[PDB]
Image 1 (spheres, chains in turn orange, brown):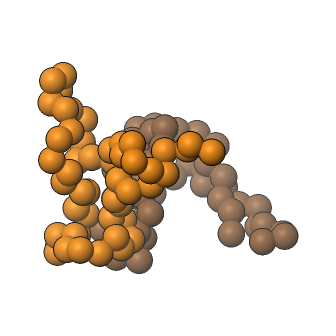
Image 2 (cartoon, helix red, strand yellow):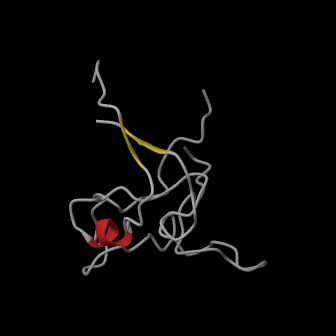
Length: 50
Length: 50
């Protein structure tokens, strides 16, 4: 999974607003703090190299 | 799992944003349609499974 890709983001992005700083989705009162819990996703997944 | 119940939502205005606000309902992301505005957009013949 060396070729990381950002499947999830805050919302749609305008052109040239590329994803450089990873900001995971927040959908709760508390921000996602070090845990990949429910409704909170991380870009760390295999890029289908099989 | 081997015998799903047959029930569908018809002629309803059931809000799905209250489900999104609810803590237990943690899966709301959508691959091909709007994740958070699914309810607002119109649709027909919604089938339910258990």
